[PDB]
Image (cartoon, rainbow, N blue to C red):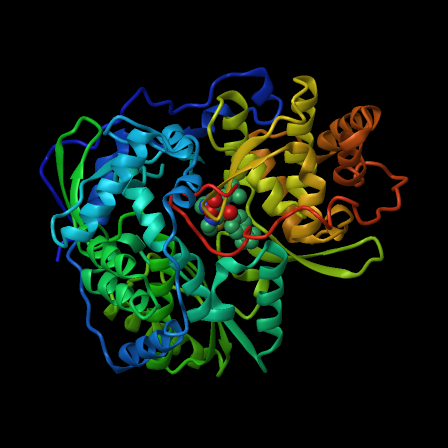
Length: 559
Ligand SMILES: CC(C)C[C@@]1(C(=O)O)C[C@H](c2cnccn2)[C@H](c2nccs2)N1C(=O)c1ccc(C(C)(C)C)cc1
């Protein structure tokens, strides 16, 4: 069937849309070619709709069915709990889109009567009505990128706030627990960056002759069929479940997940969806389960040997045993034809790699650096172009989410995050005296409230101590970074070093947590380095639940 059906009414914005980077002193000292940075808007929506609208092809075979059964068997060991109204309300982001029924995120979090009452009515309706399609809003996503030597806006689809609270009650424990039980070590969202690098490296070193590749499914969400969504539900139904939870999952699957009507911000009927909605609780879990099922079965069909998967929603990387250059090329092609039959056609044809570092998964690649003792240490990095563009954008315009904070945290060991992101943002936070003001950022889709002064502890936990002492980065990594800076008009690294020295001094002056940042975050700036020892508060702070599962589009806020 058609992934989408359009009525002709437009995908509209509910406010003016900024698309260009402003000329601002604060952002200009970081990136001067401001005209190369842009934000996607509703104006490019039709170009996206055209690409995601097509008739799906799907042929399932024995390998597919065999793999499904194996996954269901594992799912059978799971017992998921129904979340209470209070618990579900506490998981709602403070700025989550308000309901059209007289209440918003604040009311939900405060458990106001109007909100709590409407949520119950929505829940009771999910138990009684098993068929009526639930309404959804479709908006053009606003994302920042650097012009190419332009990307049309992605489309987000989500139901009303009331429905989202009910999704949590019925499925939060499931999508946070079942993926791991089913896919095990292959479930990407259970790993912190350090653990992910470790899994990649170990998996690669465990093969007698490693060969790996990333597989880019063309517009994954639109390739998800009705059958895929029901197969997904069949996996959830293997869990021990409260009666109402079971009915809720059954109703939600038929009324929301398999598809439904699309309404624009103006309240007009845009058309119909018969594929994955980006903005529902099960999207990350569902996509991970679906991608893993299709890939695992595809490997068998292509005759790939000892395929080890690493899946994060639609992002997939495979590491297996090589059988020769030609043999691998052919088997990879067979794998791709198998995925296409399962309705997971490639965006760009996959390529076999015999160098772990030449593989990009989750927009990142493994690279090598050395700690204080000169010992080799693996870490995850990526082209810094988009992160830097977004950092500049977030510097000139105040944004709800701070991808720069999320990037410092997730890419702390990288050359670019330490010398550029840390230096730039800490100098500004100093000037504005806001080092202790908590900010919002996202990690694996979940919203987090973090204070800049806690970065040191946070980084030690997610990356270890070497994150503050890495040096002697690889030439490729250094050249990619330098090249990127020249392209964007970002001052050269030597300039950042000079700026960091000044930032570190001011930080040490204020002593306290500020000084801790100066010592750990900028130890790379001073030639006479300071002996760095484990941070006291580091091995204490509660970081549990930080890397358990993905919730991209799931409207989740971890408190
Ligand atoms: C600002 C950023 C930190 C937040 C973000 C997310 O909330 O999902 C979006 C980002 C982003 C950036 N550009 C395009 C798309 N998304 C990247 C991604 N999310 C999914 C795939 S890449 N990511 C991560 O959390 C993330 C960062 C590093 C790693 C590792 C180093 C551990 C791989 C893993 C996840």
